[PDB]
Every structure is written in structure tokens, then in C-alpha cells.
Amino acid sequence: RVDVSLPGASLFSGGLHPITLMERELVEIFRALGYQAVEGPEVESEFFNFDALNIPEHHPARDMWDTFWLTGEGFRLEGPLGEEVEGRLLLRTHTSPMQVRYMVAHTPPFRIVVPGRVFRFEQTDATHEAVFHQLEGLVVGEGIAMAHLKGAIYELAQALFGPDSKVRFQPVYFPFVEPGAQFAVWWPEGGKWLELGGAGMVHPKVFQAVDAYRERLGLPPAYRGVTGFAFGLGVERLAMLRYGIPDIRYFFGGRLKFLEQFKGVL
Amino acid sequence: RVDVSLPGASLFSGGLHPITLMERELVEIFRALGYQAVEGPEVESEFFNFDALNIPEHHPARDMWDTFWLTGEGFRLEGPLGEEVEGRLLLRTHTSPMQVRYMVAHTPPFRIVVPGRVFRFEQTDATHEAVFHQLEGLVVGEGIAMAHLKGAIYELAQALFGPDSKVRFQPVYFPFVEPGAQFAVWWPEGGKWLELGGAGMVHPKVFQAVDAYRERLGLPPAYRGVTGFAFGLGVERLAMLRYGIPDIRYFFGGRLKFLEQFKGVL
Ligand SMILES: Nc1ncnc2c1ncn2[C@@H]1O[C@H](COS(=O)(=O)NC(=O)[C@@H](N)Cc2ccc(O)cc2)[C@@H](O)[C@H]1O
Ligand SMILES: Nc1ncnc2c1ncn2[C@@H]1O[C@H](COS(=O)(=O)NC(=O)[C@@H](N)Cc2ccc(O)cc2)[C@@H](O)[C@H]1O
Image (cartoon, rainbow over all chains, first blue to last red; front, side):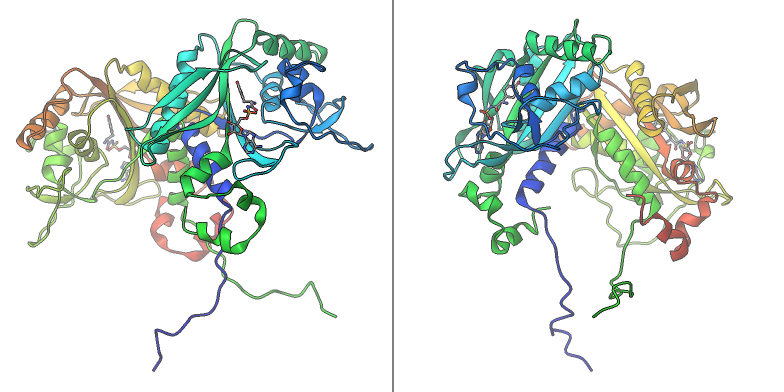
């Protein structure tokens, strides 16, 4: 006879980090809208993180970002087509550069979504980290309009908070779009707006930087007659309000007691 | 010191059945086109499997299907809205009835995909089973056209066999569509057409059966001013040519030596 209520062999039970969980749900949501997920490098060149995105040096625009500059030789940074790219190395301050990398390597129309680890030299509080995650979205093609950008975010909201959810766009500035916008989604269960990210219609100069770089590389231009929208949102910010996490600093804390609480969450 | 090349603790390693793998890839493909996966019951009523789909008794159409009829009382079969549905019980000869179940329970526009176990009383050879799986697709809404149906299958093909793949539609008969069609996809690596399934524009009488049933249930009509396409394809047939399985009869064989070969395949 056996005491069946007794503890069984202690096999380990794993789990996924909350950021991974949230990233997965976001990617699932945008995959249903036809977006494909691709990643870019964390250590990026000033050209891709800034210049290509219309953010030149010694101007108010640069002063908006808190960049971590790197040093060291022998480091090889490959470009969109495996080429050796040059320029001052840095930690990407956002996922946006992957927006230029993808476009030089592909041809429209397309829909991508790019999650990624980003870095910014700033003070860490309960809603700010120096190391966090963003999700870029980019849809380029003939006839793409801001209504499509609004439609996309509307879908995000519905998918994330149900039918009684809604979105709100307000104008904001980004050297890489025009029109530019910041957006929030209505969280019905919590009764308040959440400022998720920035977006807009890809800037004419960004498309120009892309084809110009394509030419240096010997590729034909590909973005002369197309338009497109792009957005960038905070993964931790969404995870926090979604999984009820009170302090952004927990994410990178490595505390098993914290992590293990998401073994269930998918 | 330790002989690190020695075998480690024999922890078990699992795997998923090939049908599960293939179903997952198909669902992933259609999810990217905006389709949502829902399942229906295996034991179905003659009303949903036939009558609603415009297949009346004692007519050539019925004689096309090899139905397994069931018997026994005390069995409760619930309808789209949990109601108690009546009629001669049977094993569904296809996933198509889920096409009527979903429509009475929801309102257009929408896009569903419904994988499922189906049954047919026929001889089992290397490409025929009495118990196999199908994947229905249904997209209903204002302005839906056959071009959209062709577009869908075109996407399936591209996603399944790459850019050098193509589709072929030929007319065929189904009491539940009009136009009706059968389709094949070009398998570039194998140099030959594969007859995947049937499809067409949902029949006017099917939409009528749906709303008529909705009225009995007290719901307002919902399919008067919409059109839609639907398709049904063989999962095993696609898995076979996709995973190189020579005999359909292996699937339900339960032979571990067979199954374990797909531990890798995702
Ligand atoms: N220090 C920090 N810690 C945690 N999350 C942070 C953060 N700094 C920013 N975030 C999150 O990052 C989101 C976007 O960052 S941002 O600096 O405001 N905007 C950007 O970086 C741009 N790349 C956004 C963008 C705008 C337009 C586009 O077409 C594409 C992208 C914010 O909405 C916020 O939720
Ligand atoms: N006995 C069997 N064993 C294995 N696979 C089988 C089978 N009998 C059929 N199949 C697979 O099932 C697919 C479709 O089955 S079928 O009887 O030809 N067609 C149907 O059942 C219909 N419901 C298809 C359909 C047609 C139009 C629509 O709008 C929706 C669906 C075939 O293309 C074939 O690949």
C-alpha cells in the first residue's frame, strides 16, 4: 500500500520572465495583423541610432536622449547586409534603428515588429529604468496612411483590454516622423489612460537615408513612392499595468520569488 | 574527478504528434491573416453536419459522404448557444458544420479557422483514413469575394512552400458553396501539384439556415447583407508531403518509434 497524498519526486518546474511573456503577447497581437518579428543588435552605430533617423549632433534633438557611448577596438559591427559598418559605437537608445536596418535589407510592402533591449543613461525610479525593452512597429507601402497607424493601435487596445477599450493620439515630436504622435490606450478595468508610446508617418528624410545607403551598397532605390507608419512602445510599462507589477526595477532583480509568480501566466 | 562524457540522469524527453505540429503551423499561417481558431464537437447532429449545409436526405449529395451513425440515449448534445439540439446523432464527416455553429453564435465580419477530427466510413489505404483531420476556414463580411478566397490560399501556398509556390483552383461541387471549387498548391521542391481541399463562396441557403436558426433562438438575423468564403483542407495530406510521411495509417498507429521522429520538428 502507498500514501498517495505524499510528495512526489521533486522534478524542477520552470517559467518565463515577465518581459518574455509580455513580449510574446504583443508579438502575438501584431502577428494577427500581419506583422513579422525581427530583431536588431543592442550595440549600434551612431549612424543607425541617430543620423539615419534624422537626429544630427549638437542640436536640441540629440539632447533629448541619454546615450551610453562605448569604446574598444577589434569589435566588428555588421550592417544590414553583413557589411562592416563604421561610426561611434553606442548602446541603442531605442529600437528605431532596426527600422532603417530592415528597410535597406528589404523591399516594400511589408509589416515588421521588432522587440528589443534598449539603454538610456538616466535615473531609475519606479517607472524608469536605464535598461528596458521596446517594441517597434513599421509598415511601409503604397497608400499607407495615418488612419492605418490609428487602426493598428486601436487593434492593440481591443486585443489588450477588450471591446470597451479605446485609443488616444496627440501630436508630439520625433525627428523620424511627420506627422508625429504619442498615444495612450484606455484601460477599462483600471479606469485610466496609459501612455504607451510614440508613432507617426515615417519621415521623408528617413526614406532618403535608406535608399542613399542602399546606393552606397549598390542596391536600387526602393522607397521613392511609398509611405509608412512606425511606432515604439514600452514593454515594461505595459507588463506592469498588465501583470500588476508596482516597480519597474523588479524586472532585472533576478529574485526567484518575484519571477516564480509568473509560472502560471502562459 | 569525473568522466564528463558519461551519460547523465535519464530525464524523459517529450514530443508532439505530427498532426499537432502540422495543425499548429496551419493555424499560425492563418493567424497571420487575421483568422481565429475555434473548435467544434466531434459527435454532431444531422442538422449541422448536413441539413444546415444544404445536404438533404435521399439525394445524390448525401450519397457522396460515408457517415457513421450513432445510437444511445442520455447523451446531451449542446448547440451553438448551449441549447439542447435534437436530431440523429452522428460523427461529423467534416469540419463544415462548425461553420454554421459559429455563425449562429456570432455576428459578421469575422475570420475563423477550425481544425478538427473528422470521421468517414471508408476503406483505409496509404492516403485514406476513416479517422483524419481537416481545417475549415470561414471569412464572412460585406464585400467578401472569391478573389479574397484565392488570395487566402495563395498566402497558404507562399507560407508553406516559399515564393516559387503557386495555387490552382478548378470548379467542383459542394451543396454549401456557389461558386464551388477544389484547389491545389504547387510544391516546388517536389515538382508536383497537391490537391489540398475544397472551397467556395458560402451558399445563400446556408446563410438562410443560419438566420432561420437564429430566429428560432430569438436572435436577430445577421447574414442578410454579407457574403463569404470557406474552405476545408486535409491536415494529414499536408503533413505527409511536408514531413515526408509515406503512409497515412502511421498517424494513429501509436508507434513511439514513429512519433519520436518529430521531437525535433518544432
Ligand atoms: N527610462 C525608461 N524606462 C522605462 N521605459 C522607458 C524609459 N524611457 C522610455 N520608456 C518607454 O519608451 C516609450 C518610447 O520611448 S521614447 O523615448 O519616448 N520614444 C522613442 O524612443 C521613439 N523611438 C518612439 C517612436 C516614435 C515614433 C516612431 O515612428 C517610432 C518610435 C515610452 O512611451 C515609455 O513607455
Ligand atoms: N478518407 C480520407 N482520409 C484522409 N483525408 C481525407 C479523406 N477524405 C477526405 N480527405 C481530405 O479532406 C479534404 C476535403 O474533404 S472533401 O470530402 O473532399 N470536401 C469536404 O469535406 C468539404 N467540407 C470541403 C469544403 C468545400 C467547400 C467549403 O466552402 C468548405 C469545405 C480533401 O481535399 C482530402 O485531402
